[PDB]
């Protein structure tokens, strides 16, 4: 699927980044708009964005009930007080639209102005949802309560001078606990008072039909050339995947992922500890092509020996000097001597009988079995055969390694013959 | 429910026909067959199921 | 049908007006007069069934055919096998031999 | 009780003790009946377990062949020695003078 | 003992008293140490579990703590202070038995084949059973006792648990809560939750004609009253709020603010409100009412026995809750002692070091483990029978009891619903293994291959979901919930948002989890009937490994298995290379599994590892179990849990109240692979006898068997019974002793 | 799958019999406690306790 | 109304007619780029940190495949929730401390969503 | 026999429907002699047992029929003069189910314990057209009562016995002649035996209290004996009739 | 009895309890200590005393309790957990051992070494 | 019973009248049939029928 058509260029504009707000009416369908509705007031605070709109609705229209309007207007306000009136006339004229904050981090949401072949993105400073609020009913209820209080006061014709002296007892400076203080801070009244402490800012509205709308509409564009390579946004896919998903922070417990994050001297060590029989060819693939062969050789010569072309882990590597036999409890030195004798017998002849080595090393049957099961398999009628065949190509490619291994095996055989009296 | 009943009927027909075939092919002196005939323990249904 | 007012999105009810019945809201003076017929059907479910049952063809939805019942020893049969017994390890049979309307029912 | 698995285990154990092997009784797998039948026919026994058996009491052979085989029998803790309980007059309860 | 206890200490790091300010007690760090015995005078000493078994004493480790406090407004710090003793489970991190060779086990008089996993208190071995409980923070739609289709939400946070119920008794939806005197209409609650327009509420509920027809009575009942603002609805709710009988007044009016606070935190605790903003809670309850309306039609009643809604609580969470309760009680006691002592004692300075009651926590833990009763007054949790005496009849008995699970019903009523065998137990719980009697169906055993997940962090999950196109719930109205193509994404019951093309989202999430950047235990499931995408990450869930199959071929080949056998790779490498992955019940509900290679078809997502893993531990002992009746297998498991035989290598030195041993035990001839996996052949519980299948002498009528006298004479069936007789010589209060 | 379904049926039968035992015991106790005062008299008439 | 698709959407927006249209799109929280001298910790590279000019190319492939190249990676663009209520885009320009000009930019009809292509990133490395 | 009781299923008595409580629960409900029992079964014998037309006729006569079950659509019609509710009856379904119900019978069904609906409120215009005009009752009621009317009108009884919930036509496969009986899931035996076209002399039931209060203590005892013996025989175990005779 | 237990006697017995609990002593030591306290509180001169006197009496009682069952514990470690001085503690100890004359075993040196070396 | 480990009780009367009543009324030969329907219960069983 080739991107044949519509190679739209995506431009960015910072002219109206902090001045762009997304308002939506969940109760008003997209078919009907508020273009014909005369806007009266728009009270919005810069900090803690909560806009409040005052819409004007007509009365002479047949869809409006003048009697109910007069009734609700007389209910919300006083008879002829008019000092603080929600409606100038005796009719319900203003409708209050209150806003609610959708989300805090609106940086991931942007407005996309689409033109003929180009798309301009503009960040949003905030997004609010507008809903028709019912605030005149609360004021009407408060006025009904104050009328009831006035009736309770004037229950009699003339009220004598009451002795309503405010008792002189100021609130004591009681030490408030931390829990009660936190409850006061988290109380809805405290948050409402904190939001109300910010003064309102009255702004003049301008409709879509106004020329100012068309004047400011061009500000969403950015003055720039058609094709310009951006200096940023050049991270590799790996860096992107790492930055979008940041990290949080038997002896074969370490996995391959934890294996590769280790020096080769320990990687080959734990590999020879887990397998105990490893060819050089497959070891090159396991270690990786990025590692030279000379380093792998100089490392494996310290933790392994060559037998019939195959690398076998050293006895002291599997059995530390402080450990003991899990089957018999004998010290690890005798186990290492027995394993070296087994390896020497394998270097001498490919076939080894368990009875001979058991009689020579004077070890138990289970120890001899655990020794032979590492590098040999049970072959009937002949005893045991090495698990891997002869590796001649590795010997031909590295004669000095084989020579040094044989030089070490000479002393190993000397010590074994001195100990076991072969 | 009609489909479920028809499927149950077909499966049970298969079971009964297999049981009849097994009872016909079984030779005499068979201990399960003899026990099912005498009624001491078991029945033809158990033999067909086994 | 549930109608809502464009002014405040509240529920609209029917109320008799000075000249014609109209949809009105209990919170705002917004009203909407009725010009022509406005209907809202429901189309409830009709009992299309006849509730006929007991036919011998539908009754013989059973497996056992051409067996030997211990009552009249005739091919026709209607067996039921039950396994809901733990005290009694073997299963349970219920045979219904009925061609001449004998009505055989036993264990 | 349709315990055919017991017969299969018996046959497998007989084949094993004949050939010195441990046949597996793994669920939905294990050694099949054909292999143990071949082992039986190789070792000289009947391929179905049933063998020619003579009665020990009368000394005459039985009419039907008998099913012999090594089976894993396990004894339970429920023994009659710990369940036998007789009651003489004995003691009684303090509140109500009953045993 | 390594993570959760530190969080518990951090939650109660600082404790102070109201009286005498500037005084405080701050916990700096804690340690659990190694198990020791207090036999020596004020001196500890390493002690083996076998010694604790013999001496009839507990096997616990003392807790050390370093703290800081003030005596005379002077900061005094500490380094190591006892506060109690935690019982140490065997073969744990701090246990001496871990990382030991069989020779070292012999030196400590402990069998290496012993499975462990049990505490030792006063010389007896107690095992904490795996508790099974309904998953919390999830809407449950079920038929009422009168036949109505209602809903319930058990909103459980770390502090409170509230069960909000829904009622459709009169064609309209009421909400019932314990803190409310009478159930109130849902529309009044909606108006009190911030949203006042009826059109918005209807859009949030749904746009289907039948949905509006069903919700009409609720709107009519709401319009009956004059409730049209949030203040009036809050007033009505507060009028319907019970009297809590709290010493003190309300915030502002004691009538409206109390209702607001109840709607904020008390009702739907799991649903969070940032700053008194119920929009997310509004959408949640709207989706709930929509589900109730959808269930009011077709009878798609959810079933409780579905294990996708079950959770397994181990001993870890129980001990964590108990330690939290004990630490809170200790802090309250310290605060009370301070408030009693420091104000008016004398000019001298008081300090809490003189009141470090170490016997409190130790005695609480010992009693809770021994008696088995768990009493949590902070959560009203009164449980019993959690801990049980480990059955030492045989090795198989203990191995099976170590993997037991009890039910929440605890024989309250013979419902027979949960007692049945459900398909959800596939590959997770042993179907055949179950106790015979009244406990049938309420006590179960885990499968041979299973694992229980742990609690996650849910941070990167939310980040990935937000980056995968999940729109904000507050950014849109509820009408989009009525669209058929829009699906809902949640997180452990918390509503996360909406999404389109749920197939792409599920595939991307599964691929990201297989990549290794997301924990493999995080489960994702899809419900097309409810159109909801559930993301489950809480602990207690059941997961099973499965081989990933793509394009009609398994991801694991013969070469991978050869490298595994040779030691080149392990199971964790299969988990990392996207070859084997864990699947939850809810996750496998949407996936296709194949039992064998020949059964693999085009629409296959995973391959079954091994079929015989379906059975548990005891059922594995049955040779050829698929050739036998299931009640026979159940009775066989029940009898094998009581079969006599060898217990361990240290059975001779072990001194129990009752022990049964076999004179000449023999390993079975027909052995299952499970036997070799559990090393039962090393500790058999029976013999191999030549059996004849025939009737003889009429003494084998019903289940009876005739034995051979010569066989019994030569040692066949011989058994040994070991009983314990204990006596104590204690010194009383007076200076006299038993002689 | 067949083994799982067979185990389902077995457990269903087990729980059915388990409930049936207790229910039958209770109803038997009630019925015998009710019908214990009846006896066959010599005049061939079954009379109550009173 | 039947459900549309982004490719046909752009086709009818440009090929069928030349009339402009105001759109709204959701973008990932983190962009494949580094904030240039923005005083950073691998935080989210928001659009405000970037400058003007061309930043990416919208590609429309065969069979309805639509992508957005923003450098070395390509995100997938799909249709969001089809809003039916009134969503208008306006600018609240506070030219003065106590006086501001609200300009009605237009009406928003469709909603787009851009998500990183995790499959391609995992197939790469 | 409770010990040997199976608590089985699928024993629909040959109709593959009409789930009836049988066994230990049935024995308990019988011995408790409660006035109200679960799933009451009434057996009715007809005169013209060979004809299915008369069978369905008496079925519709005895079975409770709701207005919404026969009406094809009920619509709230708002007109400029006044708003009301219009119900259209499906005459095809009326003549198909052989229900002796016309517009006049539907009108007579209304005004029966429905918030004092006056006869002048309900009107008939066509053959299957019913008009219901709302009127406020002044007790917390206004002209906006069309919602309650639309909700409660389809659930009104127009033909049959209110106690009757479901009635089915069972047939017998007798070789001599195939006869039809009625199985009614109601708890009003008096109304069943009193309806036209039903042979009341051969009408049985399962509710012991209703049979008692309808036909005497002897008929109650006979019905108890018959029901106990039937329930016992249906599950494979036999009990001598003298035991249940003494119990009754 | 056990109802004529003054608030001060209750405070004293609770002090004995917490003092023997912070030392991680077996319940037998607690029983013996509360028995010794109830026995020593029978005197008129002991019951009519100050809080310092009751506290040093609790200290001496738990000291005698530990001295009984071969449990070595120096007086310094006890006075460390008491809100008083050691001189008045010793004076009250001498007074009560002169008034009661109970058995006072000698402090064993080997057990004291065993208790003291482990603290390092 | 099924002889699978089930325990059984055994009571011994301490009065000649009780012994005679047990031998006569509760005699095994005198209770070969159940009073429910007259069907005999003490009869041949498995391994005897075959
Ligand atoms: Mg038995
Ligand atoms: Zn309105
Ligand atoms: Zn027949």
Image: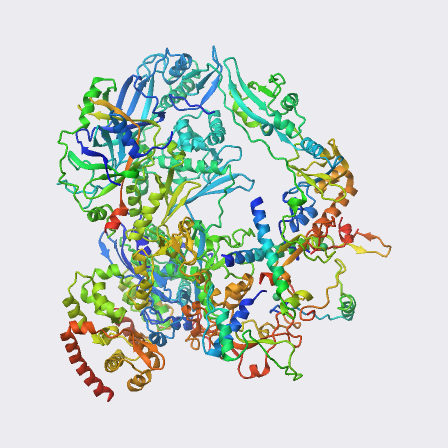
User: Which of I55/E567 is in front?
Assistant: E567
**Does residue F49 sit above or below A376 in this rendering?**
above
G121 on left or right of E584: left
Residue B39 in view of the camera: no
Query: Where is residue I8 drawn, in percent x and y?
Result: 39, 56
Quadrant in which the N terminus of chain E is drawn:
bottom left
Query: Where is residue G86 drawn, in percent x and y?
Result: 33, 26
**Does residue A276 sit above or below E76 in this rendering?**
below
User: Which of E455/G119 is in front?
Assistant: G119
D92 on left or right of E457: right
Its colouring scheme is: rainbow
**Does residue E156 sit above or below I101 in this rendering?**
above
Query: Where is residue E219 drawn, in percent x and y?
Result: 46, 28
Residue E233: image quadrant is top left
Residue A76: image quadrant is top left
Query: Where is residue A359 drawn, in percent x and y?
Result: 31, 86
User: Which of I18/A143 is in front?
Assistant: A143
Instruction: Assign ligand 1 to one image quadrant.
Output: bottom right
């Amino acid at each position: 699927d080739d991107p044949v058509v519509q190679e739209i260029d995506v431009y960015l504009a910072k002219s109206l980044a902090e001045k762009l707000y997304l308002f939506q009416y969940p109760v008003r369908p997209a078919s009907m708009t508020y273009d014909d509705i005369p806007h009266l007031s728009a009270k919005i605070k810069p900090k803690q964005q909560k806009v409040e709109l005052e819409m004007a609705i007509d009365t002479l229209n047949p869809n409006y009930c003048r009697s109910k309007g007069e009734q609700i207007a007389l209910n919300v306000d006083g008879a002829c007080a008019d000092e603080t009136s929600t409606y100038s006339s005796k009719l319900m004229d203003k409708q209050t639209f209150c806003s609610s904050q959708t989300t805090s981090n609106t940086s991931r949401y942007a407005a996309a102005l689409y033109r003929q072949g180009e798309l301009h993105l503009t960040p949003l400073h905030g997004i609010l949802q507008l809903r028709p609020s019912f605030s005149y009913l609360d004021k009407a209820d408060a006025k009904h309560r104050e009328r009831e209080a006035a009736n309770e006061a004037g229950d009699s014709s003339q009220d004598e001078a009451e002795d309503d002296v405010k008792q002189i007892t100021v609130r004591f400076s009681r030490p408030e606990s931390e829990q009660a203080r936190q409850r006061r801070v988290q109380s809805y009244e405290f948050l409402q008072k904190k939001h109300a402490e910010e003064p309102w800012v009255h702004l003049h509205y301008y409709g879509l039909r106004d020329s100012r709308s068309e004047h400011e509409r061009q500000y969403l564009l950015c003055p720039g050339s058609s094709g310009v390579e951006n200096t940023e946004l050049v991270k590799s896919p790996s860096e992107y995947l790492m930055m979008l998903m940041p990290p949080s922070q038997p002896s074969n417990v370490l996995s391959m992922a934890q294996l590769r994050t280790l020096p080769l001297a320990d990687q080959i060590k734990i590999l020879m500890k887990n397998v105990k029989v490893m060819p050089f060819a497959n070891l090159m693939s396991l270690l990786g092509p990025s590692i030279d062969s000379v380093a792998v050789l100089r490392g494996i010569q310290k933790v392994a020996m060559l037998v019939q072309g195959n690398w076998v882990v050293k006895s002291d590597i599997l059995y530390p000097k402080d450990s003991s036999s899990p089957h018999s409890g004998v010290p690890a030195e005798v186990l290492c001597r027995g394993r070296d004798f087994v390896m020497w017998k394998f270097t001498q002849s490919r076939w080894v009988v368990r009875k001979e080595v058991a009689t020579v090393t004077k070890l138990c049957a289970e120890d001899v079995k655990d020794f032979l099961e590492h590098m040999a398999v049970v072959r009937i009628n002949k005893g045991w055969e090495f698990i891997l065949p002869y590796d001649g190509e590795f010997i031909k490619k590295h004669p000095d390694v084989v020579q040094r291994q044989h030089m070490l095996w000479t002393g190993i055989q000397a010590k074994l013959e001195k100990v076991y009296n072969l | 429910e009609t489909l479920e009943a028809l499927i149950l009927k077909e499966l049970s027909v298969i079971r009964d026909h297999a049981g009849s075939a097994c009872l016909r092919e079984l030779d005499k002196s068979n201990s399960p067959l003899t026990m099912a005939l005498c009624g001491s323990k078991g029945s033809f249904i158990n033999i067909s199921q086994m | 049908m549930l109608l809502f007012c464009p002014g405040c999105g509240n529920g609209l009810i029917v109320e008799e007006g000075q000249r014609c019945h109209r949809f009105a809201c209990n919170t705002c003076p917004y009203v909407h007069n009725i010009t022509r017929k406005v209907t809202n059907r429901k189309y409830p479910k009709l009992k299309e069934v006849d509730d006929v049952l007991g036919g011998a063809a539908a009754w013989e939805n059973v497996d056992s055919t051409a067996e030997s019942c211990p009552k009249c020893e005739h091919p026709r049969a209607y067996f039921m096998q039950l396994q809901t017994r733990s005290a009694d390890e073997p299963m349970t049979t219920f045979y219904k031999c009925c061609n001449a309307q004998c009505g055989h029912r036993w264990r | 009780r349709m315990t055919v698995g017991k017969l299969i285990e018996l046959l497998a154990g007989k084949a094993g003790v004949l050939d010195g092997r441990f046949h597996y009784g793994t669920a939905f797998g294990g050694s099949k009946v054909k292999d143990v039948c071949e082992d039986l026919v190789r070792h000289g026994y009947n391929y179905l377990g049933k063998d020619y058996v003579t009665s020990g009491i009368t000394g005459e052979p039985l009419e039907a062949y008998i099913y012999f085989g090594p089976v894993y029998y396990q004894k339970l803790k429920h023994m009659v020695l710990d369940k036998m309980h007789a009651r003489a007059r004995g003691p009684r309860a303090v509140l109500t003078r009953q045993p | 003992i390594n993570v959760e206890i530190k969080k518990i200490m951090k939650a109660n790091e600082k404790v102070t008293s109201d009286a005498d300010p500037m005084w405080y007690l701050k916990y700096l760090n804690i340690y659990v140490g190694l198990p020791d015995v207090e036999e020596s005078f004020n001196v500890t000493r390493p002690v083996s579990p076998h010694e604790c078994r013999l001496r009839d004493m507990t096997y616990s480790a003392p807790i050390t703590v370093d703290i800081e406090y003030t005596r005379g407004s002077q900061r005094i710090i500490r380094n190591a202070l006892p506060i109690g003793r935690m019982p140490i489970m065997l073969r744990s991190s701090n246990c001496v038995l871990t990382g030991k060779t069989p020779a070292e086990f012999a030196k400590l008089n402990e069998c290496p084949l012993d499975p462990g996993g049990y505490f030792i208190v006063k010389g007896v071995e107690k095992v904490i059973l795996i508790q099974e409980q309904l998953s919390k923070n999830r809407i449950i739609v079920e038929a009422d006792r009168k036949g109505a289709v209602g809903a319930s939400v058990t909103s459980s946070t770390h502090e409170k648990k509230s069960r909000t119920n829904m009622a459709v008794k009169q064609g309209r939806f009421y909400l019932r809560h314990n803190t409310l005197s009478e159930d109130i209409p849902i529309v009044i609650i909606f108006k009190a939750m911030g949203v006042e327009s009826d059109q918005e509420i209807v859009q949030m509920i749904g746009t289907e004609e039948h949905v509006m027809a069903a919700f009409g009575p609720s709107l009519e009942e709401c319009q009956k009253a004059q409730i049209f603002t949030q203040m009036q609805a809050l007033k009505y709710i507060g009028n319907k709020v019970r009297r809590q009988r709290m010493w003190g007044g309300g915030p502002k009016k004691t009538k409206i603010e109390e209702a607001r606070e109840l709607l904020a935190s008390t009702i739907l605790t799991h649903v969070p409100v940032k700053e008194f903003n119920f929009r997310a809670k509004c959408i949640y309850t709207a989706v709930m009412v929509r589900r109730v309306i959808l269930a009011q039609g077709d009878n798609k009643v959810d079933d409780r026995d579905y294990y996708g809604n079950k959770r397994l609580e181990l001993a870890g969470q129980l001990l964590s809750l108990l330690f939290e309760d004990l630490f809170k009680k200790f802090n309250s006691e310290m605060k009370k002692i301070a408030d009693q002592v420091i104000p008016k004692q004398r000019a001298a300075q008081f300090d809490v070091v003189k009141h470090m009651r170490q016997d409190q926590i130790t005695n609480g833990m010992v009693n809770a483990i021994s008696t088995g009763n768990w009493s949590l007054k902070r959560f009203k949790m009164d449980r019993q029978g959690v801990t049980q005496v480990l059955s030492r009849l045989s090795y198989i008995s203990a191995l099976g009891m170590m993997t037991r699970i009890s039910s929440q019903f605890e024989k309250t009523r013979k419902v027979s619903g949960p007692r049945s065998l459900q398909p959800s137990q596939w590959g997770m719980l042993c179907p055949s293994d179950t106790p015979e009697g009244e406990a049938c169906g309420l006590v179960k055993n885990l499968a041979l291959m299973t694992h229980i997940t742990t609690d996650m962090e849910d941070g990167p999950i939310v980040k990935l979901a937000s980056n995968l196109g999940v729109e904000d719930v507050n950014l849109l109205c509820g009408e989009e919930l009525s669209y058929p193509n829009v699906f809902l994404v949640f997180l452990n019951g918390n509503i996360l948002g909406v999404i389109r093309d749920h197939k792409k989202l599920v595939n991307t999430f599964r691929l990201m989890r297989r990549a290794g950047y997301i924990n493999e235990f995080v489960s994702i499931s899809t419900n097309l009937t409810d159109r909801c995408v559930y993301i489950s990450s809480d602990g207690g869930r059941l997961c099973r490994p499965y081989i990933i199959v793509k394009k009609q071929k398994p991801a694991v080949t013969n070469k991978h298995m050869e490298e595994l056998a040779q030691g080149y790779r392990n199971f964790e490498d299969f988990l990392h290379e996207s070859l084997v992955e864990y699947l939850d019940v809810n996750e496998e509900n949407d996936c296709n599994i194949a039992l064998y290679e020949h059964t693999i078809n085009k629409d296959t997502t995973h391959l079954e590892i091994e079929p015989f893993t379906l059975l548990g531990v005891c059922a594995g002992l049955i040779p050829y179990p698929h050739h036998n009746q299931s009640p026979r297998n159940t009775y066989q498991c029940a009898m094998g849990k009581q079969a006599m035989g060898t217990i361990g290598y240290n059975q001779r030195n072990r001194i129990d109240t009752l022990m049964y041993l076999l004179a000449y035990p023999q390993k079975p001839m027909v052995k299952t692979k499970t036997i070799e996996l559990i090393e039962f052949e090393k500790l058999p519980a029976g013999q191999n006898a030549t059996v004849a299948v025939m009737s003889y002498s009429g003494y084998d009528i019903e289940d009876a068997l005739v034995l051979n006298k010569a066989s019994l004479d030569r040692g066949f069936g011989r058994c040994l019974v070991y009983k314990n007789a204990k006596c104590t010589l204690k010194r009383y209060t007076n200076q006299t002793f038993d002689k | 799958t067949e083994f799982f379904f067979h185990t389902m049926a077995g457990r269903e039968g087990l729980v059915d019999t388990a409930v049936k035992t207790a229910e039958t015991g209770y109803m038997q106790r009630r019925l015998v406690k009710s019908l214990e005062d009846l006896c066959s008299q010599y005049d061939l008439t079954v009379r109550s306790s009173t | 109304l039947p459900k549309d698709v982004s490719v046909a959407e752009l086709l009818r927006e440009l090929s069928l007619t030349k009339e402009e249209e105001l759109l709204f799109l959701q973008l990932p929280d983190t962009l494949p780029g580094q904030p240039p001298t923005q005083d950073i910790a691998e935080n989210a590279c928001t659009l405000a940190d970037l400058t003007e000019g061309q930043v990416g190319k919208l590609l429309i492939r065969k069979s309805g495949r639509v992508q957005l190249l923003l450098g070395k990676v390509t995100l997938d663009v799909t249709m969001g929730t089809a809003c039916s209520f009134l969503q208008e885009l306006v600018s609240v320009g506070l030219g003065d401390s106590r006086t501001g000009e609200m300009t009605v930019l237009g009406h928003v009809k469709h909603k787009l969503v851009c998500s990183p292509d995790f499959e391609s990133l995992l197939d790469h490395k | 026999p409770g010990t040997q009781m199976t608590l089985k299923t699928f024993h629909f008595a040959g109709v593959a429907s009409m789930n009836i409580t049988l066994g230990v629960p049935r024995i308990k409900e019988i011995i408790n002699a409660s006035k109200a029992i679960s799933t009451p079964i009434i057996t009715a014998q007809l005169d013209k047992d060979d004809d299915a037309d008369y069978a369905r006729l008496v079925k519709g006569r005895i079975e409770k029929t709701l207005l919404g079950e026969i009406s094809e659509y009920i619509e709230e019609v708002f007109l400029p003069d006044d708003c009301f509710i219009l119900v259209k009856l499906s005459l095809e379904r009326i003549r198909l189910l052989r229900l002796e119900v016309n517009a006049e019978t539907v009108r007579y069904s209304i005004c029966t314990s429905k918030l004092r609906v006056k006869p002048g409120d309900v009107a008939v215009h066509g053959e299957a057209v019913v008009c219901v005009t709302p009127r406020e009752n002044s007790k917390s009621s206004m002209y906006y009562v069309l919602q309650f009317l639309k909700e409660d009108l389809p659930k009104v009884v127009v033909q049959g016995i209110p106690e009757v919930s479901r009635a089915v036509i069972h047939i017998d496969e007798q070789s001599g002649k195939e006869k039809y009986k009625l199985l009614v899931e109601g708890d009003n035996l008096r109304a069943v035996m009193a309806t036209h076209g039903v042979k009341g002399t051969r009408t049985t039931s399962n509710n012991t209290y209703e049979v008692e209060k309808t036909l005497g203590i002897e008929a109650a005892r006979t019905t108890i004996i018959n029901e106990i013996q039937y329930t016992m025989v249906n599950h494979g175990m036999s009990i001598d009739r003298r035991h249940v005779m003494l119990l009754s | 009895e056990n109802e004529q237990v003054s608030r001060s006697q209750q405070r004293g017995l609770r002090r004995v309890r917490d003092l023997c609990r912070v030392l991680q002593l077996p319940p037998t030591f607690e029983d013996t200590a509360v028995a010794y306290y109830q026995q020593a509180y029978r005197h008129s001169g002991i019951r009519a005393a100050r809080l310092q006197k009751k506290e040093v009496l609790v200290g001496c009682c738990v000291l005698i309790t530990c001295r009984q069952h071969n449990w070595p514990l120096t007086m310094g470690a006890i006075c460390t957990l008491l809100y008083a001085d050691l001189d008045v503690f010793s004076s009250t100890y001498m007074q009560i051992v002169k008034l009661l004359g109970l058995d006072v075993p000698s402090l064993c040196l080997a057990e004291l070494v065993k208790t003291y070396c482990s603290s390092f | 019973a099924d002889f699978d480990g089930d325990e059984m009780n055994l009571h011994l009367p301490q009065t000649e009248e009780a012994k005679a009543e047990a031998l006569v009324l509760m005699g095994t030969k005198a209770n070969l049939v159940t009073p429910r329907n007259g069907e005999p219960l003490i009869a041949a069983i498995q391994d005897f029928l075959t």
